[PDB]
Amino acid sequence: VLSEGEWQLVLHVWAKVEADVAGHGQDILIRLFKSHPETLEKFDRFKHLKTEAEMKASEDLKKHGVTVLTALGAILKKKGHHEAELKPLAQSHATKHKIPIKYLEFISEAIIHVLHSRHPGDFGADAQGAMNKALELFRKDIAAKYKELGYQ
Ligand code: HEM
């Protein structure tokens, strides 16, 4: 678990992200798609995007970025007591979308990267460490649900 101090660093920087959900959202998905091309193949919706320019220019990709971050934010703000917000997500990602846990790890690295570029002042080592732990907690609980369903 994260301490009250670690959660503070996480939510303090996440408030900065909420000031521009769409901008952070498009950057994170683009980072994910460029860094790990195999994640892009999972999305029938964005499978056609070949260049980075095409990705930045897509309104639907940007719309999905909002959906991912808002859903992540609801989880983060629960500070661990996110069972009700996490279960539905794991169920659909395991059985419907078929997202392996490794991809959730890839998107966590993409999130940490984007937060560093956009908010260097409020995302130093300490804050980066806290966010990493919160994203691990996220993956840990999802994996436990995946195992239960038989997707581990
Ligand atoms: C930060 C982690 C993530 C969060 C919070 C998240 C959240 C969501 C949400 C809220 C939806 C829409 C409702 C639903 O089906 O649950 C969704 C859909 C989807 N997600 Fe994720 N997701 C995450 C990571 C990923 C990753 C890593 C992949 C693929 C590699 C992925 C692939 C998909 C796909 C394919 C859909 C269906 C899109 C469509 O056709 O509308 N997600 N996700």
Image (spheres, helix red, strand yellow):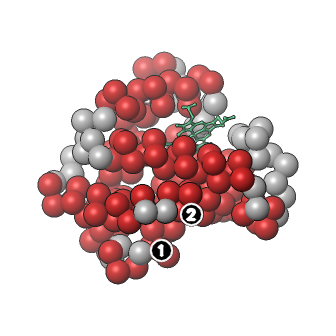
Q: Earlier in the sequence, mark 2 or mark 1?
A: 2
Residue 31 in which image quadrant: bottom right
Q: Nearer the viewer, residue 52 or 17?
A: 17
Q: Is mark 1 within 8 Å of ligand 1?
A: no
**Which residue is situated farthest in the bottom direction here?**
121
**Which residue is situated farthest in the left direction here?**
4
Q: Residue at x 31, y 35 (%)?
A: 82
Q: Residue at x 50, y 57 (%)?
A: 21
Confirm or deny contact between disc 2 and disc 1 (CB under 8 A). Answer: yes
Ligand 1 visible in quadrant: top right
Badge 1 element: helix
Residue 58 appears at what percent x and percent y? 75, 55
| Residue of label 1 | 118
Q: Residue at x 62, y 59 (%)?
A: 26
Vertically, is 79 above or below 123? above
| Residue of label 2 | 23
